[PDB]
Length: 208
Ligand SMILES: Nc1ncnc2c1ncn2[C@@H]1O[C@H](COP(=O)(O)OP(=O)(O)O)[C@@H](O)[C@H]1O
Image (tube, helix red, strand yellow):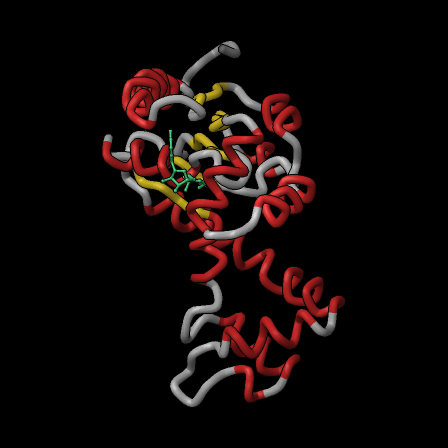
């Protein structure tokens, strides 16, 4: 069956995790792009064999686990490797993402993609939801949460797509720079619409 996909995105410290949990409490399966990226290098995964062939047998421990720290340290001191690794992992992530989408039984799925705008992944979503906050909120909330400096987070903000680039592709926007508890009511409203969209998308004769 064709699953209805709502993609969630937002910059660092905007509320991706918080919003995702709100949808999960309503019974929606969350498919998280960062979890998928870790899944494709889990013990026994096909990517591990290719990684051992390219980087050396010792990239994989005796117990079949990827030596994460060891890979990170190799790729960081060999820039093009990041690109080699991403190319290897890309198709595998696409397949695992679809498999999980296929495996989810909720009325629609929430696909959480930090790099949605950067990687133009909104082209694979039926609906785009952006959790939005002010840049200052991103700074204060990320600093607190990760115990890092303001300047450190300012660099992440300048590396990520901008606030406006995200709003340009959004179908819906949830504001999180206010009270944490206005989240439940806004998510319920969006969920109600998403149930309708998902229930009629397959037969919907004309657009919206
Ligand atoms: N409305 C809010 N007010 C204050 N803190 C919040 C609010 N919403 C979420 N948080 C916190 O802000 C931080 C960043 O939110 P989070 O969802 O983790 O961000 P990200 O978008 O990076 O996933 C977290 O520690 C979270 O608990």
